[PDB]
Image (cartoon, helix red, strand yellow):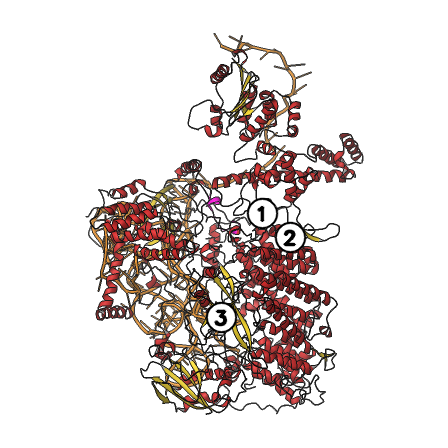
Amino acid sequence: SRRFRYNTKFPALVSYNKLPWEVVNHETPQFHMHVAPHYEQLLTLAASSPVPHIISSKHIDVPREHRLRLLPGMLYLLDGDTLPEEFTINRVLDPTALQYYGRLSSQIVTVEAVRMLVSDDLRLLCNCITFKGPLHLPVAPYASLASLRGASSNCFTLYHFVRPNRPPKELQLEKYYIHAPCVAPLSEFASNSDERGNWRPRLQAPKRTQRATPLPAYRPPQSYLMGLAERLAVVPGGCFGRRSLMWGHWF
Amino acid sequence: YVVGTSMLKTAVVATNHMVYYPKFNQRVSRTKRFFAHDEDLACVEGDLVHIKQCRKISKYKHYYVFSILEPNVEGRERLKLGLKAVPPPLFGYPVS
Amino acid sequence: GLNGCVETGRSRSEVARDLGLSYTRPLHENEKKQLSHQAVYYERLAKFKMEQPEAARAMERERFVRKFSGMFVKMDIRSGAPDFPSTYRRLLGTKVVRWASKRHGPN
Amino acid sequence: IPQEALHWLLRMIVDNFNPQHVHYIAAMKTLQSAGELDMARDVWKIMERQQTWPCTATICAYLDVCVEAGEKTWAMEAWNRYCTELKFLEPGEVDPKPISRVPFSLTREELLYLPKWKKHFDHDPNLDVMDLNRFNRTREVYLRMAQVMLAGGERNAFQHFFTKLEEAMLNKPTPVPEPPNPHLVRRPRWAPYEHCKSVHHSPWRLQNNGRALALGPSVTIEDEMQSRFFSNDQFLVHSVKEVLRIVLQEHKRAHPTECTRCKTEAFFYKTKDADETLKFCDDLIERLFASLGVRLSNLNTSSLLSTILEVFRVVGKESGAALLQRANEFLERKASLGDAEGSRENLTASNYLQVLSGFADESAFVYNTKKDGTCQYKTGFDPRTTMRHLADVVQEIAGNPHVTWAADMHLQVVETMVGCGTMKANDYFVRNVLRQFSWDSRFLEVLYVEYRRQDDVDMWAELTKRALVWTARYNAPASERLRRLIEDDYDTIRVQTRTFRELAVFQFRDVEERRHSRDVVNELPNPWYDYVAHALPFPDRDAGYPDEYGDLGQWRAP
Amino acid sequence: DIDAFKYWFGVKRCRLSMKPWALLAKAGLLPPSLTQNSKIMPKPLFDKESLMRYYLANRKDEDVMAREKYLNYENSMVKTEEERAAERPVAPYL
Amino acid sequence: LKAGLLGHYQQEAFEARKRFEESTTYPGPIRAATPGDTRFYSGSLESILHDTDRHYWRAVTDDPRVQHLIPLRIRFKIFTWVTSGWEQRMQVVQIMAPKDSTIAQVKDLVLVENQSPYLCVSSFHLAIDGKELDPQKTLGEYGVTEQSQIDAIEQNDHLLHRDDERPRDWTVDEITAEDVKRSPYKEMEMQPLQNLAPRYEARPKGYFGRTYYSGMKQ
Amino acid sequence: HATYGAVPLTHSQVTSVYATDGGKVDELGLLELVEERIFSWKLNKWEMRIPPNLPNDQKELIRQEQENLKQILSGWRKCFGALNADILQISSLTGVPKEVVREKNRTWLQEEVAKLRWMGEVNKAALLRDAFMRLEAFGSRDFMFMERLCCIYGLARQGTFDEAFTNYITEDPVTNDIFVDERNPFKELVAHIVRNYSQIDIIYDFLGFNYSEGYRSSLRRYMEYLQCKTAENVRASGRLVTGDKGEHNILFDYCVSRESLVSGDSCQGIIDFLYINGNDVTLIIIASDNPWLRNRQLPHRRQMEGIARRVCFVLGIPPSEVRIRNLLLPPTYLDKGSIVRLNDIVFRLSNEQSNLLIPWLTNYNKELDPKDVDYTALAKTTNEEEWLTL
Amino acid sequence: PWWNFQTEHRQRCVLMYGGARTKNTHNANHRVFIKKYKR
Amino acid sequence: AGKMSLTLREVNTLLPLLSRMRRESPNGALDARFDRVFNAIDTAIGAAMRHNCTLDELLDLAEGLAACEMVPSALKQVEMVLIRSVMMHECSPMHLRRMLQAMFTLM
RNA sequence: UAAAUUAUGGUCAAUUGUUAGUAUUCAUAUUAAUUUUUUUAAAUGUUUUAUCAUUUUAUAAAGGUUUAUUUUUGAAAGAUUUUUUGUAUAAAAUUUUAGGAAUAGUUAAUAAUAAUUUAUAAUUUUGAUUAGAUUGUUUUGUUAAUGCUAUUAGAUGGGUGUGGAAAAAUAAAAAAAA
């Protein structure tokens, strides 16, 4: 009788991607907030493991009709800065948006430029980032990034295709997220290193006469505190830790 | 007993219960009518059915026909003939 | 196919359906019409919506607005009661005049 | 607490419910996983006292409990009572038996002439045992019985069971595997609300959302099907692996001090019965190879190889390098067998872990022996050779990209570095496992010994404090052993390790408890605080009530 | 009702008012209340260093501590080797 | 209905059942049919989410959910980095393909257990000792068994068209567990569930207090 | 246990399945082993013994048969336990080895009871006396031997019990070696039974064990067997077996009374077998379980006269020495008295002659179930009747 | 002694309502019916 | 599960597919997996023999049953409705020959 | 038509206060009274917070009329975590009136959330609908009494759509985050 078919406890909800306050606009720094760490981890993975389809030819040439269906969510690296076809280029100059590549620019690779390429039909988007110089990370001989001339004429560019105005789930790179170890501290001990018998193992702790130097005398604060952080449910310093384990805060 | 089948996928079953009057030490049998549910239209008027309560199916339908204990052979044969399961009565309720 | 399943709780009808049998009374013309004109109206409505979408959009907007901007859309217990006029009798007459009677069925 | 599983099984009885074989299996499985083998046997005894004949899956669960507990008498009673009459599937036999019992129903005549107690249905598992046994698990039953007899020491019975099992699996077909039934849980069809916080929700650490495993596994797992989906020869490989596993657990049970790492100097040297144990295991492996022959080349043996490496590394104490050599020789033997040249497969993480553990055992030591602040190492220990071999192995594993590097592998690498005495274990930990893995505090239990050898006492202390801050920032609590290790050096480094609340409650509780024990009067029993009497819902005897009859002044009869 | 009190206090983790807490402390079922404070002894003063010194001076060992905790919270019917042998089945094995 | 006639009707039913058991004498071995499901659960209505389509306790596994399948092994050409560089090696994946599946279906299944982000990334074709297999040919027509060395040659294309629209755990029962991190053949499926809380009975039925006279049962 | 293709077995099929050759084995010892195996069971072991995929009528009949077997085995279990308890009691009271207690006599019992009563233990002496008197009636090492062996043969016939007597983990009593014992005492004992007792099926059906067909066919086979050993040129057919043309030794199985008798008809003559020996004629009828049909089953005097007259016409025997005897038998089994009387009047052979001719009749011990007095009275009257002579 | 079910009911009422079992309500109140309409 | 019901349009839609699978199977028959498919088609035929059915639908049903070599439990009702169709005006020799071929292939 | 058999050879009893439970006064009880007392005059301080805000704090009365209900998991309890997944919405059954009849935002079916559809629909003389009276209520009282009689637990579709839940304009107090 269309009223006694089911319960009403869990009704249909409006899709999460049709609410403006849930969709990330690509013209704001919040877009670059969501993607930068994925680029950092992808470059770290590419530096230490051969990932299959990350280094490629000029550009993935899919038909103009399948472009927006097959292309979005796809990522690839290329040697030298060359931009795809049929795109309008917008170079982001906003410091509030460029601040989010600081850990990418310093600890992985110096970033030359960041640009947003909007399709002529305004339905697909390409975040493309040009890096310069060699990697600040050690690159393995087998790592797929070691097959790039620009890394290790010295600039190479990453491209990441995504749909505009979608929730932050679009801006997710999960499959490029497997932690492969980088063997830096073991090569010296390995047989491949002639700096192999030069290290003297420490099997025993040295006999210690001195005790650890005492810390400077503890000075109680002199300002008005907000209360007990453990009581107010503030994690240590509001930064990290556990409410139960209070530390590094006042007292 | 199935009493009416004018509604689709629904059987009206007349059921009886007992009320007790201590003063007169009496056991008088009352009657109650229930909308049952038979999805395949297998109940004919005059069937002795076993009915069981369940979830609600309609505004007034919270029972179903668990089993037909004694079908109306005459009713089925009349329906084969193309008549009504039981000839309609000639008396009824007054209009005023 | 005349006895339901005591342990699974299946009715006579489900037992027969699982056995592959058919215990259906001979239907009259009006009953067969009831079982036949379910598809015709669906096809008519779907064809209407496919053929002239301006009027279909208008009618759908009317329905949606009339529902959304409607009172008693909470899906609380009062709205969820099956028989409002009989479950809530004291409301009728002196508070609610939608129903002029408190009994519409065997209950 | 684990007792609660047994309590909830008993509430089913007290509520006049008939627990099903699935309830019994679940209770036994949970209690065994919690380690309460006596409670598991109590569950079995409850089943028997209820007089429900066990499905073969219930038999298998009880036999697993018996295998782990090393009790052969339990399994022998179970065998004589139930497991006998079990047979392997024959070539002409029907693969799954047709369902026999028809669901309970009553006709119009039975509903009238039968009594209520006969018309009543209560889901009795005895009615359904035979339709539960539609699939042959006698293969599993025989494997479990062989394990039980081997653990109990009855080698003749072990040989009986194993020979019967192997000849059956060489000369008889595979039975159809029982598909998993998804009606045992009440999960929702889909997630009602899509929240999916980002992996990088925290600006401090990297979290693991419900969508993606975004931190790297904390434990290595084997990539294999379930025991029921194996072929006959595949399950024969599995049987050899499992009897080796039982040999291993019995060796560990017999010599608990030679199998726990860095506890006593006996850990370094193989015991007296190790040679006979290894001879038995190796002759069994050769028996497997001879029996299967060329067919073995098309059977996955990663788990068997991992078991072989573990049994040789624990019972046999062979070096990690020799362990890798044995693994490579086994893989090359398998590849060569089959006349299919120019194609050999690689080791997996499941056995790369075993070789790394062999290296870690090589480099292990006895910490703070005889209060001398000196760690006693194995005789003839060569840190440079061990480090060279480990570095080569790690480079090979990294060069192979199809190995997933769970956290335990990095743990063995770090432990080997610390034991070998190189001062780069902390650097490797920071670069490879700090931010990219969900690491426990055993890593820090090793890195603390690494730190203790620092030239500067202040460097030692600061490294300890930074390790604690890491425990805080990345959600890895500091374990009791790590905290005690750091406490034992409170005089030299004054690194506090106990909370200002924990120490106060310790003070008060401990002083009160010592005072209470030393007092004599309060040692007397207290019935009000000692126990609960009759936690059941109803009285244990009839107080006379109720009175099911009215009264003269009462008209409301029913 | 001591059995029901233990049920609701332990498994249901219900709350306890101070007046009932004081009344029950008289029965040996609970410790004296938090507000049953003697006017004479002032409240304690805690020092981390002294507390640490005491804890190190007499700290329990890992296994004894864990076994006391297990006996108190998780289980109390742990059978001896003698009881396991008694329960173990005998020669005929049927 | 008059209850006094219940005894007479019981006698009549007994005699009728005896006449039935005595006259027709046509029982026999009949295949039992799967009991299907019933829409008439008791209590109040259930929501869409929990409509798993079974409303009674059935402790058996009927035929429709049982499938006949063979444990095939599929070989892969993988390259490992040894000190020299890029040594060729072999990788295998365990697949449980139904006996009646086609080679295209087996390939599509292999696409689904390739959790490895490195193994099944480019279009490949199945072959036996080099001889490529017809993708619309049944396993029985090729005679392939578990002891059949079968290789996957990866043509160096890209953008392998995938459709995760079919859940890894799809049986005729149409269950959809959201987590697809492991195949049903690999999942143990019997383990303690920590995502829940055990709940005790906090609602006394009839007995609330000092004296258990009768317990106000019902 | 029950199997999808398991089925019940007939006598020929049982003999074919257990067709083994043996020369020497102690029936009593192997039977004791098999009975201890049975007694060392739980009630569960009797559970899944009905083969599935079998029609409901045969399924229910097998259920009655197996329940009867289980009840008889339990009764013998209780009797055996009580007998052993009395053995231990006598051995403890007297001090004699319990092994030699089974060969003592009333003189020894008297002397021991006198010693006990002299030592001042009157209650203990009474216990000893009661135990010995109760045990001299139940202590024979082969007490219900035929019943026990027929029960084992019924287990063999069921076809689902072959596998419950092996695959047991035992331990060597002396060396304490745990092993799996695969010897099948049930197989050996059933092979010996089939080899030796060529008409164990007849004994099993006579005892009332067969619920499917009863004992009528086995009775016909037994009667034909005795006819073949009593005549010297015997020709048999479907329903008629004849000896010589001068001795008038004819057996004729007329019909089946149980199925022939309809409950709503009025006819007085329905007989199972008709046997004429020389000048005498006998009508053997198995009394139907229905008391309201036994009366229509027993033929009338004038119908008996007509049968005699037709016999005289056909076989030319003078009407002078033609005499008919009507014979009634129990519905579902035979009594020992019934069998001896059947031999006495139908075949005119005495008790010693009967036991010489068939060995097992000597100790075939069966009694009329006291629960049915109607049959006892009717059979008493019919067997006490005189030869109707015309 | 043995108590009625009324004792159990009174116990339940006392426990739930805290001693409130009854009020000893006046029983002999003299009611009257006042007719408003015509005969 | 009873959440659906098939009419002759659905049954005629399905039957050709099952016949095609039959012809593509190594033997002539389908796996045991399709027992419930055929049982549902059987119950649908049995039920819809009571409603009002067109000549084309009946003919297609007969041809599908012939193709799938499936004899329904409502064979009697099907042949009765075929009798109630043979002598109609809409019936032509093409329809009659198809009906006779299907009935021969079945019976 | 059974016909009066000769052992009469065993008498000597009962009572010892010891209980298998509705018991009847047509006038004594039972009520307003012979014995009715005692007070009561409104105008009002919950709290913590980051401060013109935010967090915690869900059944007062009169009136109107009352089916015969309710475990929002959603807040708290509460813990080594984690869900606003921890099945709360249902049914059976018992009512009154000196002048006794019609009722309807209507019944079922439905690919129909939000019904352009289909049907010979549904309630009622086994007493409906409306109107009148009207919380229920083995608890009160009375009696030899399955009779008569009496009653106060509650609940509340337009006042914020907030909240886990409207129960929200008053709070003998159930102590409300040191």
Q: Tag on residue F152?
A: 3
* Residue F137 vertical position relative to residue G238 in the rendered view, above or below: below
Q: Tag on residue G44?
A: 1
* Residue G233 vertical position relative to residue D141 in the rendered view, above or below: above
Q: Secondary structure at mark 2?
A: helix
* Residue type at tag 2: Glu
Q: Tag on residue A37?
A: none
* Residue I66 drawn at (x, y percent): 34, 51
Q: Secondary structure at mark 1?
A: helix
| Mark 3 vs mark 2, CA separation in Å | 51 Å
Residue drawn 66% across the image and 68% down it: D311
Q: Is residue F62 magenta?
A: no
* Residue type at tag 1: Asn
Q: Nearer the viewer, residue J85 or A134?
A: A134
Query: Range of the magenta residues?
Result: D115-128
Q: Which residue is mark 2?
A: D77
Q: Secondary structure at mark 3?
A: strand
Residue G220 left/right relative to F175:
right
The crowd level at tag 1 (other Cα within 10 Å; few <14, some 14-19, many 20+) is: few
| Mark 1 vs mark 3, CA separation in Å | 54 Å
* Residue type at tag 3: Ala
